[PDB]
Amino acid sequence: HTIGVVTTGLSFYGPSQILVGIERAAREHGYSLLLATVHEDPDEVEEAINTLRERRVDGIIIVAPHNSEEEAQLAQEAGVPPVVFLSAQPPGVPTVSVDQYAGARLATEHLLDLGHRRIALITGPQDWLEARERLQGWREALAEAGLPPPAVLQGDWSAASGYEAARQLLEQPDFTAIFAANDQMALGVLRALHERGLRVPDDVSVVGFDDIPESAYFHPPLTTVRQDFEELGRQAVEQLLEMIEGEEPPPPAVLPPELIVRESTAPPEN
Amino acid sequence: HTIGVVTTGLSFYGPSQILVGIERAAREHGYSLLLATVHEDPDEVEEAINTLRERRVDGIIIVAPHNSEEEAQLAQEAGVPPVVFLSAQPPGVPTVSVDQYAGARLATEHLLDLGHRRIALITGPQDWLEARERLQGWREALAEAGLPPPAVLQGDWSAASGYEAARQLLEQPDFTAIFAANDQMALGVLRALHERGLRVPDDVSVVGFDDIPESAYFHPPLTTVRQDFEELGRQAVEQLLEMIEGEEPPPPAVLPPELIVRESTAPPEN
């Protein structure tokens, strides 16, 4: 009958677009959504599940991020009615997620295949697993090309932090390309480069991550890695419905990201 | 003790930033928030108020938009416990809102004071009161300068729609400036202009609306109208607390917007 959803009302890209996929897939299978937004607290996560079990909910999707320690918090051990996690901790937990490492490899290998060696990284905030996995993908793509990691500076997902980080990198312009760990930070990188009089991609190539709707309209249109958030929520409903009507715990589904090539990359200049 | 909030989990700018102001003001006065997100339906709005009256909520803020007909829907007439509306219908309803007309006047008068006559408008979607009020501000600013309305094309708040509209305007380039009714549409306008080989502001001036965090990082940094959404939510709590502890229904508060002048405007070329 009904499906519960717990989420966070944040301005970061992803959650609201996942919810569109949940709305679209649940309505197609005859289900309605029971939305209960929470904060970033484990106690509010648990008692949202209790208050959504109060109404006749046949299954609940968790979009609020937890950890790689969901089981060791009396969150998965206590939750035996059908729950799917939109986070990365599968020791037996049915999850669905985007392959962040693979996405960062796509972005970095795109630049390596163009001839770039000095690919700097504007990495995401340390307390996000997605950020840490994207740095690992960038580092290992470079290592497998025989190259040491160039400069890294950490932002916080905002355009402001991408601008500030790029300005610091430009004190030592030892790079021909910048991989920015999301599209918003990439926007700030582009402003720092343009302020310096540097052309994109003629002087410096730039790649982002997310494929937010605005990224095709940056100057220049941004090559980026698409997270298909709507498909993430649709596969969250599809995975949950096997456990509503009764089936085995499925393998943790991993959505491969896609590189969207636009106008912000080129071979390095001579 | 507790304060309830109803809202919508949409990707449009505003709601999540209002919620930051509600969280900050309620925590300062010792209150906690009870969040219940809904869809864009009057029946879900009413029964969210019923299910939030279930928990010991001392007052509830409504961030989900309603209409200019909130009273004639058994929504204000039925709601006698303390409710504040973040919408525009004050026949006796305590509301708080941003002055959309005044903001559009600021944007258009900025361009008129620079010498522009042919100020085209990329207007917002018709079913948003904010969009209709911004068009009225643009039209009346022009009228009070003695000028007829130039070309108008309607978008849908997306950068894509601003790009498509600007491309259509460029089939008849009878404008020296474009007022885009939000910052995202302005981003698409900038791409359409740059694709045409037109310089901003040397060939065409552009003004947006919202002051989203990204707007300072557009190419060029965008002159825009700031909606102080955090102050909107803080004044929503402050207005609600006069009616929790007992006071008269206050006047409908109107927040004046502020023009943020950056690098996207200049006098028209000769």
Image (cartoon, coloured by chain):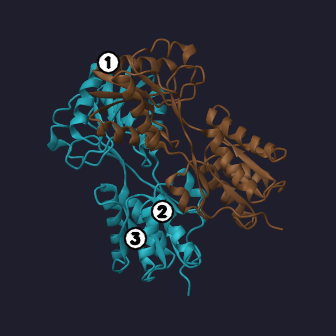
Chain colours: A brown, B cyan
Q: For the residues marked 3 and 2, what is the alpha-carbon distance in whole angstroms? A: 10 Å
Q: Is residue A125 visible in the rendered structure shown here?
A: no
| B240 or A63, nearer to the observer | A63
Circle 1 sits in a helix, a strand or a loop, which is it? loop
Q: Earlier in the sequence, mark 1 or mark 3?
A: 1
Residue A141 at least partly seen: yes
In the image: residue B129, left or right of residue A138: left
* Quadrant containing the C terminus of chain A in the rendered view: bottom right
- From the image, tell me which residue sits under label 2: B208
> Chain for mark 1?
B
Quarter of the picture containing the N terminus of chain A is: top left
Q: CA distance from mark 1 to mark 2?
A: 42 Å
Q: In the image, what residue occupies the spot 41% across and 60% down? A: B103
Q: Is residue A189 left or right of residue B137?
A: right
Tag 3: amino acid? Leu
Residue B121, numbered circle: 3
- Which of pointers 1 and 3 indicates the residue nearer the eye? 3
Q: Give the quadrant of residue A190.
A: bottom right
Residue carrying label 1: B56
Mark 3, secondary structure of its residue: strand
Type of amino acid under label 2: Gly
Task: Please identify the residue farthest to the bottom as the structure is shown.
Answer: B270
Quote the CA–CA distance across marks 1 and 3.
47 Å
